[PDB]
Amino acid sequence: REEDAHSNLSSVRKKLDGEISNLKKEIEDLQLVIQK
Amino acid sequence: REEDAHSNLSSVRKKLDGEISNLKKEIEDLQLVI
Image (cartoon, rainbow over all chains, first blue to last red; front, side):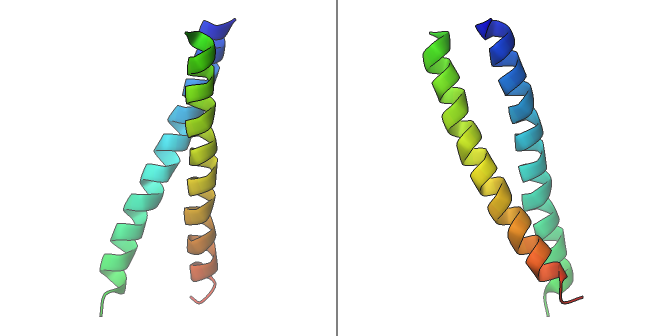
C-alpha cells in the first residue's frame, strides 16, 4: 500500500514542483519584459 | 517509516498547494490589465 501510495503522492508532487518552477521562472522572464 | 513519510509528503504537499495558488492568483490578477 504505502510504496504505491508514496509513489502516487510523489508523482503528484512531481506535477506540483514542476508547475511552481515554471511559475517562478516565467515570472522572471515576464519581469525582464516588464522592466522600464 | 512510511507513515511518517506519508506525513512528510502531505505537509510539503499542503505547502505546495498553498504556494502554487499564491503565484497562480497574482499572475491571473496581473494579466487582467493587458
